[PDB]
Image (cartoon, rainbow, N blue to C red):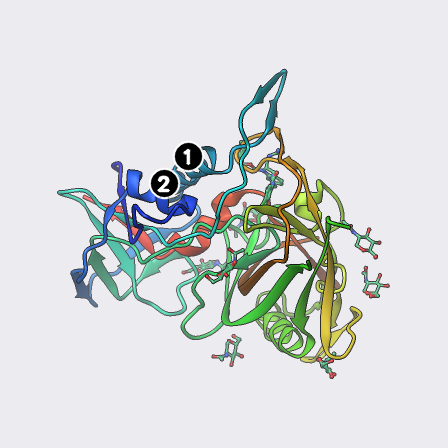
Amino acid sequence: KTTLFCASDAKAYEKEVHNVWATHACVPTDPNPQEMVLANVTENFNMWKNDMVEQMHEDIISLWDESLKPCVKLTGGSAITQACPKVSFDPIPLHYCAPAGFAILKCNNKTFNGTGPCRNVSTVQCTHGIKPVVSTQLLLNGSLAEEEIIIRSENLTNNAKTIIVHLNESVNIVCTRPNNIRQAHCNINESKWNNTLQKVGEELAKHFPSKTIKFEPSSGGDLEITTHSFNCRGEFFYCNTSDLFNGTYRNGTYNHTGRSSNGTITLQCKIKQIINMWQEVGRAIYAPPIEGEITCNSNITGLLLLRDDTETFRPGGGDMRDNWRSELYKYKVVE
Ligand SMILES: CNCc1ccc2c(c1)N(C(=O)OCc1ccccc1)[C@H](CNC(=N)N)[C@H]2NC(=O)C(=O)Nc1ccc(Cl)c(F)c1
Ligand SMILES: *[C@@H]1O[C@H](CO)[C@@H](O)[C@H](O)[C@H]1NC(C)=O
Ligand SMILES: *[C@@H]1O[C@H](CO)[C@@H](O)[C@H](O)[C@H]1NC(C)=O
Ligand SMILES: *[C@@H]1O[C@H](CO)[C@@H](O)[C@H](O)[C@H]1NC(C)=O
Ligand SMILES: *[C@@H]1O[C@H](CO)[C@@H](O)[C@H](O)[C@H]1NC(C)=O
Ligand SMILES: *[C@@H]1O[C@H](CO)[C@@H](O)[C@H](O)[C@H]1NC(C)=O
Ligand SMILES: *[C@@H]1O[C@H](CO)[C@@H](O)[C@H](O)[C@H]1NC(C)=O
Ligand SMILES: *[C@@H]1O[C@H](CO)[C@@H](O)[C@H](O)[C@H]1NC(C)=O
């Protein structure tokens, strides 16, 4: 309804690039924030049409332009060349704050699916701290649901609409390029993956009740959406999830179909230099990988799915506003 500002813990003395950007663009966080409950009000939210998401998307585009400069950027006809130094890159949390005379309304219902009316509301001046993590298929390093796994969609009957699964317990994923230069792998505990994909099948079943629930690898598209892609320490990883989204949930029981080995699923990955950009339609070329071991240890805290008797779900992604939505869903600017 208005333009918001960001607050952060960044420090002007980190040269990590999120820190640099935030110290120029954000104000410091209030050490003790005000929050004002109101259990009577009942207030309508819509996470799928929330202008906080558009403002955040702008900010993160700006951060990546300042920070992860490509050697070449192809946008349509044009090709732009610049210095592409290797940088230190680790996302930090960002708070979005309402300016003077507006407030941010927070929905306090633990199972609120992001849509419709909400009974227990609050007024705050800033959101919680949201780490702007760019990735597909798996949402990393977010904040888990309080109670049960929530299923969010602008419209579950429209199978073109992305489904956000909000996990209530996180699942560890560890990706490494050991000391090819391009070759890397990720490891997930097959047990924890089994467990969470069962519970996700249960919630999906509540919404599609006759049908069998199948998980299957992403069909087609750019490598960025057909693998789980993400930035780790500056380098762009592309990890094959064919052994991860691979399993059936038949009779209130889940059966994993993908290959494990000693109780860990291992995704093969490549570090790539030609990137399809998430900010706009365009390509970006980066320098070859840094030296040594490149490792990220992340929490899978949500999933992005697309639905095709039987209902089949494939990993989705590609529109980073859904990443921001998965965090901003309980908030609304007012007044
Ligand atoms: C229903 N939604 C389907 C969908 C599928 C695929 C995409 C979108 C949307 N895009 C999308 O919405 O852009 C936002 C937008 C919206 C409206 C108008 C313009 C732009 C992307 C369009 N950009 C290209 N074509 N170059 C494409 N996504 C990626 O390229 C991607 O994620 N790359 C990547 C790079 C690095 C990392 Cl680390 C990473 F994790 C991922
Ligand atoms: C979310 O809840 C609303 C009612 O609050 C309901 O109308 C809508 O269908 C639900 N959507 C999903 C994806 O569960
Ligand atoms: C998370 O939610 C699921 C499904 O809604 C439920 O079965 C499970 O017990 C919950 N787990 C935890 C750790 O709260
Ligand atoms: C969402 O789903 C379908 C589109 O397939 C359509 O009936 C309408 O847009 C929506 N329906 C409901 C119940 O929201
Ligand atoms: C879940 O993973 C463990 C580890 O391999 C396995 O022993 C167990 O049988 C699996 N459960 C399934 C596939 O339902
Ligand atoms: C992932 O690996 C499988 C089997 O190794 C292969 O068939 C599939 O095409 C791969 N997908 C991508 C996007 O690399
Ligand atoms: C599941 O994994 C196996 C081996 O890891 C693979 O052969 C199979 O094609 C995968 N399922 C699908 C639907 O791709
Ligand atoms: C997730 O957070 C951990 C701890 O801050 C970090 O080491 C890891 O690299 C993060 N993952 C991504 C993809 O940013």
Give the Cα separation between the discs numbered 2 and 1. Answer: 9 Å
* Residue shown at the point (66%, 44%) measured from the top left: 224
Disc 2 under 8 Å from ligand 8? The reply is no
Image quarter (top left, top right, bottom left or bottom right) of the C terminus: top left
Q: Position of residue 153 (x, y in %)?
A: 52, 54
The amino acid pointed to by label 1 is: Ser
Pointer 2 and pointer 1: residues touching (CB < 8 Å)?
A: yes
Query: Which residue lies at the image location 56% right of the left edge and 32% below the top edge?
Result: 70
Tell me the residue at 23%/53% (across/down). Answer: 29
| Picture mark count | 2
Quadrant assignment, res 213 = bottom right
266 relative to 176 in the view: left or right: right
Residue 119 position within the rendered picture, expressed as x and y whole percent measured from the top left: 28, 65
For the residue pair 34 and 311, the one nearer the viewer reads as 34
Q: Is residue 144 left or right of 101 when viewed as pictured?
A: right
Figure quadrant of residue 216: bottom right
**Residue 51 visible here:** no
Q: Which residue is mark 1?
A: 62
Question: Going 50% across and 43% down the picture, which residue do you hit?
Answer: 87
Which numbered dot is residue 21?
Answer: 2
In this view, 200 is above or below 123: below
Q: Secondary structure at mark 1?
A: helix
Q: Is residue 69 at all visible to an observer of this figure? A: yes
Q: Quadrant of the N terminus?
A: top left
Camera-side residue of 65 and 218: 65
Mark 2: few, some, or many residues within 10 Å (few <14, many ≥20)?
A: many
Q: Secondary structure at mark 2?
A: helix
Going from the N terminus, do you reach mark 2 or mark 1 first?
Answer: 2
**Label 2 amino acid?**
Trp
